[PDB]
Length: 123
Ligand SMILES: O=C(O)c1cc(S)ccc1[N+](=O)[O-]
Ligand code: NA
Image 1 (cartoon, rainbow, N blue to C red):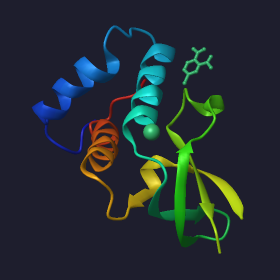
Image 2 (image 1 turned 45 degrees about the horizontal axis):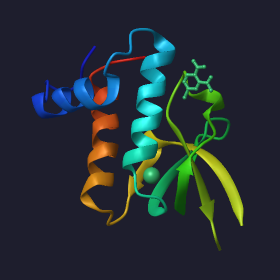
Image 3 (image 1 turned 180 degrees about the vertical axis):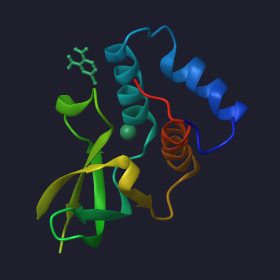
Image 4 (image 1 turned 45 degrees about the vertical axis):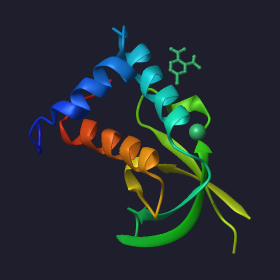
């Protein structure tokens, strides 16, 4: 189900800019992957909530978000590659990233993705 009400501005943009003619799961995933890759301005900084299910703990890491992760798990979720430069590179779910002082378009694209998930939409 949906945890937020429809936002028609986001719906229009998703329809016309992102999903476009996509019909099946792979096409819907691909649309989002290319949109995010095109619209997020890399690199940017974010707080990553890196969770450990086994120990019930959370490490909130401050990282550079370098780009989309290579598209191996594209069908399931949107992943980005992040680095802590204190170099260790990781794969993180975009939905676990809180961007820090980014430009308007990057913030918008992240919000669109968060909105899609909140609505309960899936590829
Ligand atoms: O093959 C790919 O590399 C592929 C990548 C993405 S992001 C989405 C769908 C795909 N399909 O369907 O092939
Ligand atoms: Na980009």
